[PDB]
Length: 48
Length: 53
Length: 53
Length: 105
Image 1 (cartoon, helix red, strand yellow):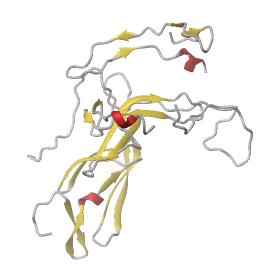
Image 2: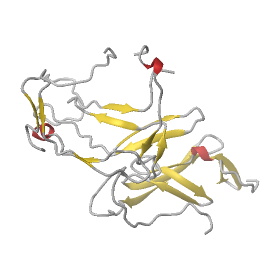
Image 3: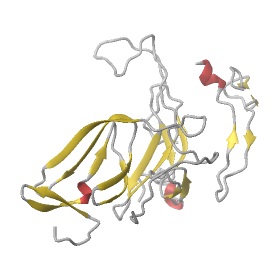
Image 4: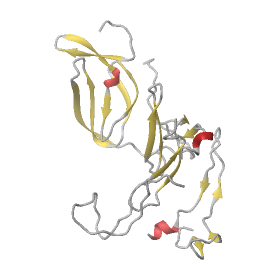
């Protein structure tokens, strides 16, 4: 996560996808139905 | 397309800030912001439906 | 930040503000704020105005 | 100018006489247009974007724009240990001070 290669596939068209974003579901704010989460930013954007 | 939105409707959604520093349920809200393009163009997904009356 | 809104049928303004970091990547080896009358052309990505599937 | 109460109107001095004007023409600006949260008499409450100047103005009964600009350093204090530009949908809640819309005075 946060590094180049966080999401990978063998070919652009492939349905076989590896990902490691450390996505964690968090408790919603009281009175709301929104779904909060903690996730690393794309390693691709950082690399660029 | 105009042949797609015929069976759909606009919806209300919660916003973290409705301009007064307070949250509310708005007729307009941002579902997603996308910036894949490198020319600086932004794509914004909203609860509003534009081009359909 | 990014803010989007519209005017209601009752002439009431509605908008929502969300946090968003907007700072487009540099194309080429120079940092410019607008496209020049004279210059070179490099590869970049854009969104097409077409509404086709 | 008739001493009645009308939330849609403001009155201003014009030479030797008071005159009416639309409240809709009232604006507050710094580095960018400010949001007005409420008004009464000589006091205006507004939330302004960060900037080094502050100005106020309105359109009069003759459709002439009037304004006044003063220097003013506007840079709100940081609440908590993070510097943010907008209110989040989810987060922690900390003590702060505000102005109440109440006119009890």
